[PDB]
Image (cartoon, rainbow, N blue to C red):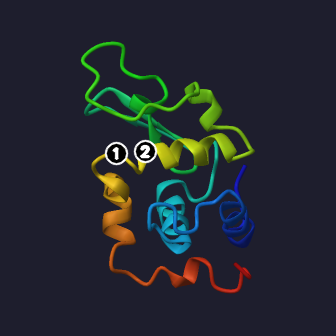
Amino acid sequence: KVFERCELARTLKRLGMDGYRGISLANWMCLAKWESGYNTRATNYNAGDRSTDYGIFQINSRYCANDGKTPGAVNACHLSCSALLQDNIADAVACAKRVVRDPQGIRAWVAWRNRCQNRDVRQYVQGCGV
């Protein structure tokens, strides 16, 4: 599913993302925009550490597969990785909320640091009535 921008801004608002952990709605929109272009089915393989990023927020398999040995130290999600590719984003959001509490917060995603941080994020929500 590829979300239209306001449709996603309103869905994220309804799910409790606005201000979650002090993270603004415009920041969550900016992230999803750069990470997946608002596509739920987006997947990205990391050759570097033999891991896969799933869905709208490009959440790492560490959180849904949970590497079977030498597990880093993450706030794993209570779902299988496939749950991160479905049309209804609720599972995905619940999982992103887990992720965000990890020691890197939103700085965990590089795309956010490069494309969103200190940048005008307003644009992503303008005229969505959120």
* x and y percentages locating residue 73 in the rendered image: 28, 31
x and y percentages locating residue 53 in the rendered image: 45, 38
Circle 1 SS class: loop
Query: Given contact means CB atoms under 8 Å apart, are the residues at marks 2 and 1 in contact?
Result: yes
- Mark 1 crowdedness (10 Å alpha carbons): few <14, some 14-19, many ≥20: some
x, y percent for residue 57? 52, 50
Amino acid type of the residue that numbered disc 1 sits on in the rendered structure: Asp
Between marks 2 and 1, how big is the CA–CA gap? 6 Å
- From the viewer's perspective, is residue 31 above or below residue 130? above
**Which of the labelled discs sits on residue 102, or is there none?**
1
Q: Tell me the number on the disc at residue 58.
A: none
Is residue 7 toward the left or the right of residue 77 in the image?
right
Q: Is residue 70 above or below residue 115?
A: above
- Label 2's element? helix
For image coordinates 33% across by 79% down, the residue present is 118
Q: Nearer the viewer, residue 90 or 40?
A: 90
State the residue in front, 45 or 80: 80
Mark on residue 99? 2
Q: Quadrant of residue 117?
A: bottom left
Residue visible at 31% across and 65% down? Answer: 113
Amino acid carrying mark 2 in the image: Val
Q: Quadrant of the C terminus?
A: bottom right
From the viewer's perspective, is 50 left or right of 89?
Answer: left
Name which residue lies at 53% across and 83% down. 122
Instruction: Give the residue at x 28% y 48%.
Output: 103
